[PDB]
Image (spheres, rainbow, N blue to C red):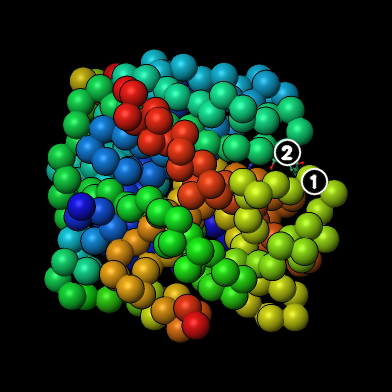
Amino acid sequence: ADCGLRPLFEKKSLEDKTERELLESYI
Amino acid sequence: DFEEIPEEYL
Amino acid sequence: IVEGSDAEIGMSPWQVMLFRKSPQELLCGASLISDRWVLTAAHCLLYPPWDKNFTENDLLVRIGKHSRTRYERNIEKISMLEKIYIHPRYNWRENLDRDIALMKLKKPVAFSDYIHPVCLPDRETAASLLQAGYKGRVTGWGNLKETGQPSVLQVVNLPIVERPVCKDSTRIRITDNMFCAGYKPDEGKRGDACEGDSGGPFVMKSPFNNRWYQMGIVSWGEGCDRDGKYGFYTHVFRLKKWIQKVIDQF
Ligand SMILES: CC(C)C[C@H](NC(=O)c1ccc([N+](=O)[O-])cc1)C(=O)N1CCC[C@H]1C(=O)NCCCCNC(=N)N
């Protein structure tokens, strides 16, 4: 339900240093 | 090499 | 993890460490999937060729950790095993087919900034993200090299590889319950899971709902980060029926 949403990142709208690399691979 | 954990944890 | 990097604090709050009681050592990685269920590779608890058969009392789960060796006071939580559940058709004899197991905790773990469950995929998350080219993220406290150890949690992003290419990289018989991930030699980029990363999660972030899903479990490989070779992962969605059955029943 809140699965998958990290307190220190998603929940605060902060991105970690490499999650963008994942996104750019999802075409 | 691993730090001991609380005895409560065994 | 070979050729990865230090984790950020709270970067993988579902990360679990399987820890041997005596001698106190790292057994494997694992994942938190609810406040009482932990997912791992079956080979972490059962592998007869190597005389591995662990029971509940031989270990504990350490959640919310970053440092490998440190007891992280006021951050990690250490939990006892109520009951271990291995896939009844886990094939340790030949190729680690259905390399998956569940662990129910004695008591619920409290979520925190450092402790949080990952989602499990449904059929569409799977179809949508489990595509050659698409990268996942693998985390663990395993070996930094095929043959040293990290001070803190390691992370590496890796692309899922085409099925024929996976099959052509090994003499091992691959099944639909597995996928492989890693860079080709020609791609230049490197990285792989390694010894000790076993049972840890391969996660992907949905671009649709921005949630992290665990698509794979670190299962096997032939060496670590070798050219022409790929890491193999348990296909979590393909074994979802068993997961829900265990959890629905127990
Ligand atoms: C290939 C088989 C299905 C089983 C497999 N054993 C092997 O056949 C194997 C093959 C080659 C080497 N080697 O060094 O060249 C080592 C092991 C193995 O991986 N096993 C045997 C039981 C446990 C599991 C394992 O160690 N898992 C460790 C996970 C390491 C992840 N590796 C990578 N991502 N590279």
Q: Residues at badges 1 and 2 in contact (C-beta under 8 Å)?
A: yes
Q: Which mark is residue C95?
A: 2
- What kind of residue is marked 2? Asn
Of callouts 1 and 2, the N-terminal one: 2
Please give the name of the residue rendered at 76% of the width and 33% of the height, measured from the top-left corner: C94
Which of the two residues, C75 or C160, is positioned nearer the viewer here? C160
Q: CA distance from mark 1 to mark 2?
A: 6 Å
Left or right? Give the position of C201 relative to C232. left
Q: x and y percent of residue C110 in the render?
A: 15, 40
| Mark 1 within 8 Å of ligand 1, using the beta carbon | yes
Q: Is residue C43 something one can see in this rendering?
A: yes
Crowding at label 1, few (<14), some or many (≥20) Cα neighbours within 10 Å?
few
- What kind of residue is marked 1? Ile
Quadrant in the rendering for residue A10: bottom left
Please give the name of the residue rendered at 67% of the width and 30% of the height, measured from the top-left corner: C91
Badge 2 element: loop
In the rendered view, tell whether residue C187 sits above or below residue C56.
Answer: below
| Mark 2 within 8 Å of ligand 1, using the beta carbon | yes
Crowding at label 2, few (<14), some or many (≥20) Cα neighbours within 10 Å?
some
Q: x and y percent of residue C167 in the render?
A: 78, 57
What's the chain of the residue with tag 2?
C
Is disc 2 on the same chain as disc 1? yes
Within the displayed image, which quadrant is ligand 1 positioned in? top right
Please give the name of the residue rendered at 18% of the width and 75% of the height, measured from the top-left corner: A13
Quadrant in the rendering for residue C121: bottom left
Question: Looking at the image, how many numbered discs can be counted on the residues?
Answer: 2
**Residue topped by disc 1:** C172
In the rendered view, tell whether residue C56 sits above or below residue C238.
Answer: above
Please give the name of the residue rendered at 74% of the width and 28% of the height, measured from the top-left corner: C93
Q: Is residue C218 something one can see in this rendering?
A: no
Q: x and y percent of residue A3 in the render?
A: 25, 53
Q: Quadrant of the C terminus of chain C?
A: top left
